[PDB]
Image (cartoon, rainbow over all chains, first blue to last red; front, side, top):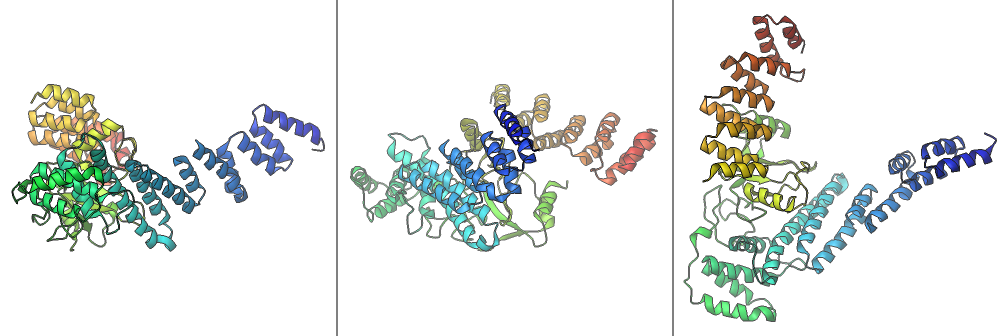
Length: 392
Length: 125
């Protein structure tokens, strides 16, 4: 142990010969933790560096800042690295900048994905009791923004392209969903003029001529860009020649109370009678024959699943043990949110019309549409995860 | 309505649920079995219920409930149909995580058929 020059020459040759475990044993015999951490960072042994950073917290910044920067230069990896650093506020700020840039660039589908990621981060932060209520409010806010930008992207594409990929009924439904969901303060980059113009055009094509007149009258209260003006004037002169009725086939039935609801409701996204919230297909935005329900007090979510699996041969709907036993697993859909949120249960009232949910983002779809969209894109259209992931 | 080609292309698309639905509506029981065995345990249970509702192929119902891991309903059907070979295969897969009442019923069956060593292992479980 007195032969420091020979021992350091052995340690430096063991480093030069890519043998960091025996170089490390030699540095540990000499007592040198500073050379040990540099040896693990330089040999890129991140698992051993992280193990030393967990044993000695003073090195966490020296390991994870180089790693997060390298991941950012090669932003999604930067965010995962800010998350692993415990600096949740900076992770959110970087993602908020990227969302604002995506909106400014008219990349509304990427903005929707980043707003969903911001929502999931807020839910992870809400696990701390001191920020639960505020971060749950931000979670619902960013979840709503993710859905608004996901809908608006289809409308924007229709208005900027000389053709539509989307069906007229899909664009009609999306336009109605957006007008119901838009606050008094329109979120940045979203256009009410574009949404009302697509609603007016598709309402004319589908035979909803009172709704088309209403959309043109609402357009007259807004500043209209010069490129749309001729089309909106011609449309306003054209709709005056059409009858003053709307097609009965377009009218949203509430599946809970069997009430027919007006094509636009001033109460946002609910039935005018029972105030049940409408649940919409994340592909087509059709209302889904689902009703949300709640467990009776003293049933656990694990117990509720076991009762649903054991098949025997505004006012909320509350369900008892004996009703859960009578229900088929095909008819019940379950959203398995992370902890300070309880699991949410939904019943299909039309078992023949198969509904599917993404196991990761918990969005709901017609099964044939979800199967098709997943097979086309290799992933969920909303969260970009492959079918290989069953996790939230 | 070209069923055989629709089933072929659904199977190639790995969309076993649609192929199962289509096989059920047209009575393609042999393709239904092969598709169910490739699919999820829930689709195996649904194909097992279809074979129960027909009544003709009650061995396929036992096999699909067995391969879905629903040992209770597989044993009940295997007792009701007197299928001794299927009971022996189900019993070989009953571990200490299985219900004590099912293990006791299986042990009484092996006591009645002189297989005392297996009856002891199930009584211990």
